[PDB]
Length: 135
Length: 135
Image (cartoon, rainbow over all chains, first blue to last red; front, side, top):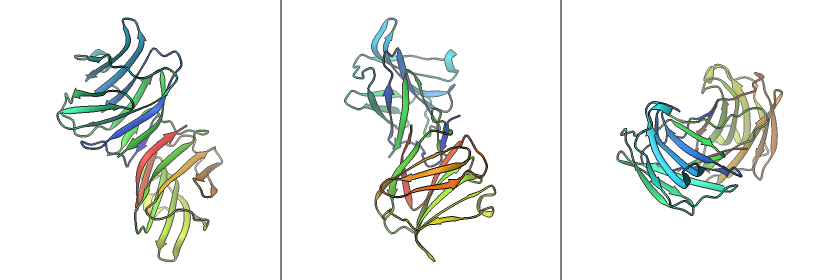
């Protein structure tokens, strides 16, 4: 399951853009990059309506999947809308990730595990991934 | 090396579009889909200037990498240019692959190994992959 795109080496200095469509009536969706679904250097969750989190961005990482979520960083500079096309561009160096949301904020999150190569990408939740661009 | 895009299941009925830039002064470049670099259901080679092949499309498959190339199918309906952006959309069913080159031909090639899922994608040669879209 998944597609291995040989040519795409998401190393320090590359810009990975993901694009797709948010569902109508979303709860939340995330962009996840790391080594596997269990070992994520960045989980970028846009929470539309998720209990106490209403239009909040939450960023975190985990080495133990769902049971290893660490210190959350949150932003209320929420610019995405239900049912719409989105694009988020990620890049990083050994110190940090730089998150450029199209027509929205620019955020930074620590590169907590000092990664210089990230082999895995997934979108989770109420959105559909349709494009991956690497430059 | 490569990026695993979890969400992209290139199954029968999906449309995979690859986009990128052809090098200046190219010899040839290919789009390759299959199970690995050694086991390819489709190798779609655009040969600009490759000895006797001058602006010829060659399509083939292999189960043994470079030593298992099978019966080539060729087309001279060559529409790509050096230095330019290209996009090719692939889809398939159990019988065949359908190759839609943007502003160029529509080609078909047999699905020789009766595949219904293709886990691997690579571009090879004188071009640079910049986008992968799955719909």
